[PDB]
Image 1 (tube, rainbow over the protein chains, first blue to last red):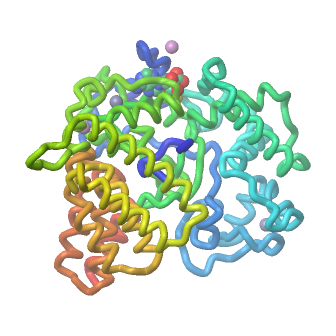
Image 2: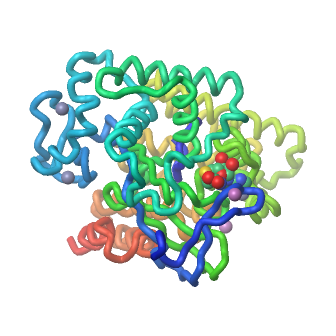
Length: 10
Length: 430
Ligand SMILES: Nc1ncnc2c1ncn2[C@@H]1O[C@H](CSCC[C@H](N)C(=O)O)[C@@H](O)[C@H]1O
Ligand code: NI
Ligand code: NI
Ligand SMILES: [Zn+2]
Ligand SMILES: [Zn+2]
Ligand SMILES: [Zn+2]
């Protein structure tokens, strides 16, 4: 995952 | 004088620092706006959005040197130059060899901004970048190796135009970027880029947030999605709210180093339906369900990696397969089924199979409205996509109904005068 603040999981 | 009207920074017990409302805010009310301290457009959207202001416009004029950066006009081209200059010459120099991660690209810009504007900017009225939380003390070996790899990439790709601090300052900076950074998504939640919004970064997380962050070009905007009373803490969501409590918390613990204790995480009310199992004669034994949950969550990561090495047909096969295996235990409304249906929809959209995507979307939409909050961009974007698909396939009635369902949420989240809304209303009148 390792994402920044997000609404949709990429 | 007050830095941000009707709000104040405070110490939120158990959550470090936070943002508090001083006055009442109602649904759709704008709490505040925050210009980007630093931001970078994703490579894939180049030529579609202006590098400076993010306006999505046709016939954008490109940069003469790198021919990679596109702009509205010369003013936007010139205004962006202090930042673009960090990549312009290098993309020419390093050809296809130039693959800095987005985060590294963002951090170079932050470093640049610190150098140009050391004083507090208008984007730092309550919280400054230098103040960002880092959790350096909680970082493990792997995360640290990853940060060093990012630092190495930054040196490799940015050394001639940017002066660097000692290694520890870079470790801290990357660590702050990791827990205070944002992604900018368009009206369909498509990834546009990454940015730093310091005042927005002050708000703590909840899985049932009372505000939504949206973007107007590169301007961050914060609007209420529930009633906010004076003295109440203001909460946004850092993550995708579709998943069950454990998943959300595994991600929050993993990326932000805290376990959420909001009502949804405490009561877990949405979990039963998110993990809906189908009603059979047997029924499924608990062990098998726990096993299907592990399988589903395993396939999520397998799928996420495979986007990089597999063809669309194959990814589709993964989705059909996974759904088939999981459907032995799981009901269609279950979020793990939905993740795969959603991904499958995305593949369909990629292979231009509009009918297939529409057939998945119609199946995805209802359970989404249940799992997500009342005003959720994840739901709105879905209604929007469904609507545009209907409109494109010449089914105007359903198109209007879906666009109206999207608009009703978007008026709250983006504000009535947002250009996206005018665009969607302008799409209906055709
Ligand atoms: N809901 C929550 N529960 C506990 N800690 C939270 C939280 N939401 C945010 N945090 C904390 O805040 C960080 C995100 S940046 C938010 C601002 C931060 N609290 C500060 O004082 O600067 C997280 O890494 C986490 O440690
Ligand atoms: Ni404090
Ligand atoms: Ni809720
Ligand atoms: Zn522009
Ligand atoms: Zn250039
Ligand atoms: Zn929570």
